[PDB]
Image 1: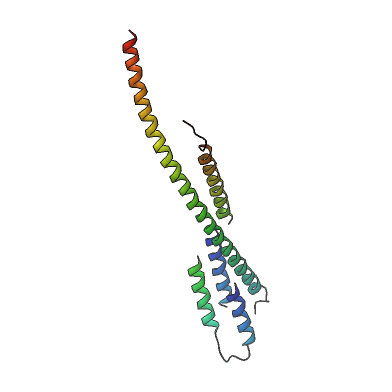
Image 2: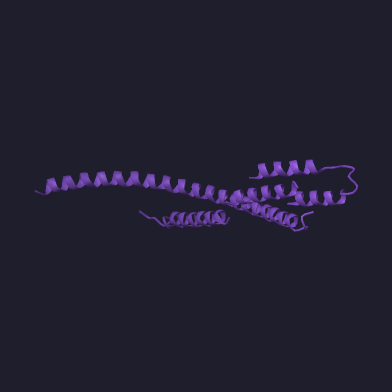
Amino acid sequence: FLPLVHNVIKCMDKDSPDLHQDLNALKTKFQELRKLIGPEQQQQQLHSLREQVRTKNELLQKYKSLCM
Amino acid sequence: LLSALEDLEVLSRELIEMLKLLQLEEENQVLELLIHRDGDFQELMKLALNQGKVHHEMQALEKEVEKRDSDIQQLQKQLKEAEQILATAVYQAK
């Protein structure tokens, strides 16, 4: 999250020299990014899907040899 | 899963930044936000990979279902023919 670090750096550099106060802009941008962005459950689901796809491919290839 | 955790971490970081506080709470919030961003990136990559794998598996399953339907129709025709032949044989056997 480079935005929070950049906001903290700007607030620390502009503590005494408050020429351009972008604290509100940074907070609004952070809130908007958090609203727009939206555990290992996804990884487990992906592993299960990969295993199921491998099983389906194996089952499809099991019916390759067929004479009559 | 990762979406809700990343959103909660970003909300906590924004609430901490809305307000120093011993230079500890801000650093902890920044670290939590960075970890949440990394986890969200990893989760997006995993979701893209899972969507690709799901599309591939759906294509394979559609092909298998078409093959199974064709085989079922062929076996049904063959079974009807064999039943007719068996009836004719039982009739002609006497």
